[PDB]
Length: 563
Ligand SMILES: COc1ccc2c(O[C@@H]3C[C@H]4C(=O)N[C@]5(C(=O)NS(=O)(=O)C6CC6)C[C@H]5/C=C\CCCCN(C)C(=O)[C@@H]4C3)cc(-c3nc(C(C)C)cs3)nc2c1C
Ligand SMILES: *[C@@H]1O[C@H](CO)[C@@H](O[C@@H]2O[C@H](CO)[C@@H](O)[C@H](O)[C@H]2NC(C)=O)[C@H](O)[C@H]1NC(C)=O
Ligand SMILES: *[C@@H]1O[C@H](CO)[C@@H](O)[C@H](O)[C@H]1NC(C)=O
Image (tube, rainbow, N blue to C red):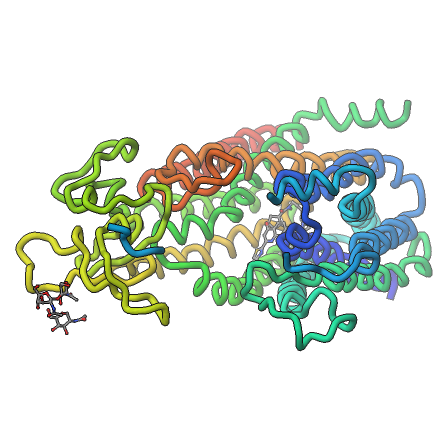
């Protein structure tokens, strides 16, 4: 079978590598409640995976190429697997877990601090998590380099497309098992599950991070086994690392992809938030289904992109042109989102006054209306109640409603002072709990967003394999492994970490309501002005793509001249 055998082992690693990445996020919430660790330190534990990966990825790629490549992938995979077991050890070494809107009137940090003194189990998760990052280093730079050197004729692109196609399954298997395990209690098998009172919907409930990280670890350990058997074939660092740079086509190409990948990565991280705020439509009904139909199409694009490159005879200049064509199409489709925007959310007490007689320019220092003034209720509390009129209110207490139907279900307030607007005395002022449902005309618009979103992703998916394929050709044959590593480090150090963080900083200015944390001045933002959020999130995302497209035109001219 020649190089085909190697592909099978590599594809298995790709499923394992992606599985490790998704699992940490799918269980991160459970870990915090279980270890009685401070919220601040939590980001740090999540960060542990990234630092391990970034620190060793550039060094290993250059050094790794000289050494045999099949085995190395194996050592790293194997290390990853040990980390997975290492990450979940605490559960086996810790005792049994211990549990411990309104009508108008008319300590966690301390626990962590105690734990911090001397030695605590939170260090174990961090250590183990870092091991996964170290283990990841030789899966893409060393592995991808091997396929290119020994591929026959122009077949390398097609093989890469297949691996990505297989790689997409990783998250799929990971959400099934990941969520399924969450339904299982953390000490399953140890404690009699008939006495545990907390429920999977309960805040207290702690998920099985130990089985969540055990399956990934076991999967990674088993995945390594084929590699060891495989045959080898079917001042040095500083000098070489410099040569990767001062290579006009290559240097701008890495900056070019940092900007484009950041836009895509940034968009993916906040798309659910954007969809929820702009169209009211929740991800609860969206992500649950749209997140599915999407996987095969995204996977289909990756394979098709690889196939298109393989079938046609494409040179290095040709590949770039094809990559640019996807980018032009992606941006044009991306630019279409601005046209399809619903009207701004109307909330009493923020965009407009509680009475609703006239709008207020600034949400801050909003003077309470007469209906609002009669009831003395806290401004900070948030409880979106939808009135008969259709105007959202900050809280039922703020609305002036003093009656409830019982605790059985959202109690349509018997009367609401603000809701019963002048001219409709007969009409009821009762309100229903939950964010006001968006108007029927707007819902139709939503679908337009989702249809283009799937379509845009597919076009992005078509060119997704191109970035990796293009990079190998421009750089000299000797440094292929290193070039990918430097590019991989740059994409996952800035695109991976900086993009969401600066997006959040930029996005927050638009936000109009701040939830009050016990310690933090601002913990979460309840609602964002829709036009401001749309203009800023899409605009920043689009601006990056426009810059990305501009680089391609400059690059194409440069590439054509050299070749
Ligand atoms: C790490 O976690 C992520 C990261 C990014 C994701 C992403 O954004 C895009 C997919 C992602 C990617 O190709 N992922 C994989 C891969 O193979 N990268 S690669 O570099 O190997 C490839 C050869 C070029 C499997 C990950 C391996 C390494 C990531 C490399 C980081 C830089 N990079 C190229 C990206 O982030 C890209 C951008 C999209 C998605 C999607 N999720 C859905 C579902 C769940 C609703 C639809 S699309 N998941 C992602 C996950 C989970
Ligand atoms: C709104 O509140 C009023 C007062 O509690 C409700 O009931 C009556 O008020 C009128 C005028 O005083 C009279 O019919 C009686 O004094 C009250 N008893 C009833 C129930 O008739 C009114 O029904 C409420 N409207 C709602 C629930 O939308
Ligand atoms: C609203 O109140 C009116 C009486 O004013 C009553 O006839 C009607 O059935 C009520 N409808 C709802 C939605 O409770």
